[PDB]
Length: 68
Length: 68
Ligand SMILES: [Cl-]
Ligand SMILES: [Cl-]
Ligand SMILES: [Zn+2]
Ligand SMILES: [Zn+2]
Image 1 (cartoon, rainbow over the protein chains, first blue to last red):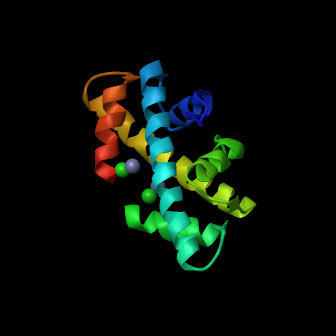
Image 2: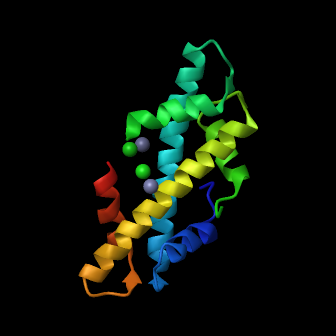
Image 3: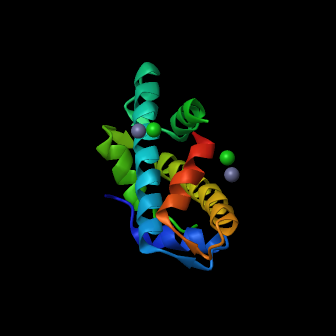
């Protein structure tokens, strides 16, 4: 796992939760990590079809549209 | 912003990118943060319709299904 748990716990508290189980924080961190990886994988293929090696913000923005 | 950028950069490198612009890392961190907040907001309403104050892993798992 790359994402730290603490910041994910703050997101859920920030959205209005009174109490958050430790298992809720870990579940959302793993779901967002898996989303990040699938978006990143699609952004890499977009950059390669554009002839580039550098992943740019427009690749991320176009890749997220396949998941919406 | 709650999520740190560095770990998001590692996710994109881990998925296979050779080089990542700083703007790509920031864009994906903001998209995952916004997803985390919308999931968390829906999980809070599920827990309240179940009569609970504590957000649990099953609330997260049911809330992500509205976005798939
Ligand atoms: Cl998926
Ligand atoms: Cl949205
Ligand atoms: Zn996946
Ligand atoms: Zn939203």
